[PDB]
Length: 214
Length: 213
Image 1: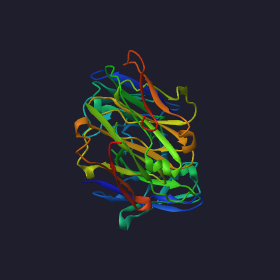
Image 2: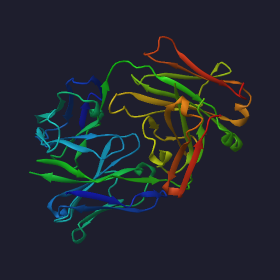
Image 3: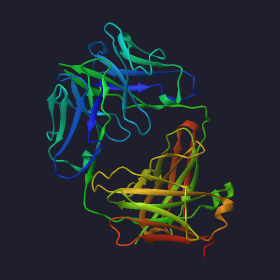
Image 4: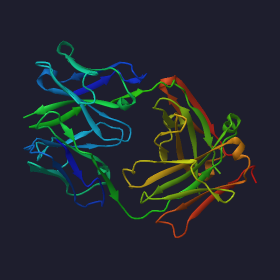
């Protein structure tokens, strides 16, 4: 099967550098062009650069020219995006994709990797219960973390029905917050335990919070 | 070259035909492709070279056009078709994406179930108080959620978040979070969220009185 697998993303200081990698399986990268496409929070898709590894010809979006360098190592079947002089505008999920031709389109895409450009320090979340009180609702508030993302599960993955984990929101403090909620039988509140399992990889924070009726 | 998509957004019922248009500032021959993107996920190729269905894509998707005027058509819209759809021209470098068109699934009206949550004792010790209101499983997305503290309407101290449309029943859920200092929180008794929605005959209010009153 054809697969593109990206790596190299994360949190960087403004003015800093980061190199993204796109490793291809199931085809040779010199057979096509390889593109990088990004999506900033709440915005549309933006093309950033392409390369034809057969001859090393390239092109860049005007906003990235000089500062970014696209390259390829055919002996590793991998393409790269060297990003320098990073600005907040560059914060985005970065995708790589192959362009196939017969007349064509981008048929195989990488999974995406999140690049956050900021001077703010990593910070793990505080996790507070949203206590219940027939259907009853309960949840956890995951507050004051940086950067994204956080993952939330319930009862270590045993509870998935009726779960709603909301998108993160940037607060005026520059830190993220989100809530996850679930609806359950009202009759279960006293005897069944409900635990919010929160993971924040960037700060190596793992928290399990029991949510009880108050 | 500029790719202008129309409409910017649309809603249509399950089974209906949806048409999205992409117009180019110059002749791009037939070098135009269409992509579906679900929130947080890699785009997926639907149509290439203006009219060709990419292998594995459902037969309900089709594409037409040449020169300066291109269209993507979904002949029978399904609940899983909610996404942002993008055109891209690749006749000349640089390739250019359209702005995107958000497709929403229209369905019957459904009133939200409303829940309110006081701040935890743990949070109160930190010096801050968050009050959360949940509106669960409703349609349409449009909802007015108002905070009242001791029956006084609140101004610039809440933030809302909405889930993506449910893939099976096409509903939304919404959270509104009111954030106050602990000092301000402890000056008032009644915390209430009032919800106005097309599915509700009159506005629904859920409240609690601080100090388990």
